[PDB]
Amino acid sequence: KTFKQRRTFEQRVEDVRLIREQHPTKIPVIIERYKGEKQLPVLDKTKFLVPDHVNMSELIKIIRRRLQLNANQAFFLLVNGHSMVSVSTPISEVYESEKDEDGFLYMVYASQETF
Ligand SMILES: Cc1csc(CNC(=O)C2CCC2)n1
Ligand SMILES: [Cl-]
Image 1 (cartoon, rainbow, N blue to C red):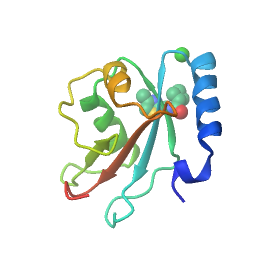
Image 2 (cartoon, protein in one colour):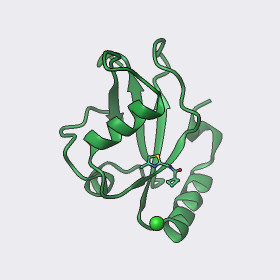
Image 3 (cartoon, rainbow, N blue to C red):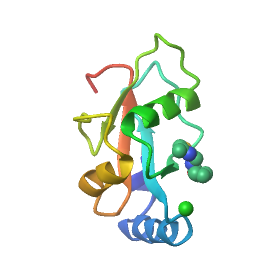
């Protein structure tokens, strides 16, 4: 059902290696709905190439636009299983500290801070 479940560690690693070869300025991001989530829709896809210069505040804006949310729908984004200490950090920096061992950066969204 989830991404890690669909693809072998081997497959996720080789894919990250190809994105490096072909999309060298992009951060390979996995963005998934919380398995409890009722209110927000599922994304049209799972794997995203995020320009390495955008900060987390702008990545939240991007996903809210992708979900076609309105002003007073709530949106919370976990990175590597936990809260973001800051939304102002560039995603290149966030990748280097919060990346998975397979080389993706893993995010999960919900309408409550209680995931
Ligand atoms: C910044 C951002 C968020 S999702 C996105 C598009 N994601 C992709 O799969 C590729 C097409 C070129 C990047 N762009
Ligand atoms: Cl590129």
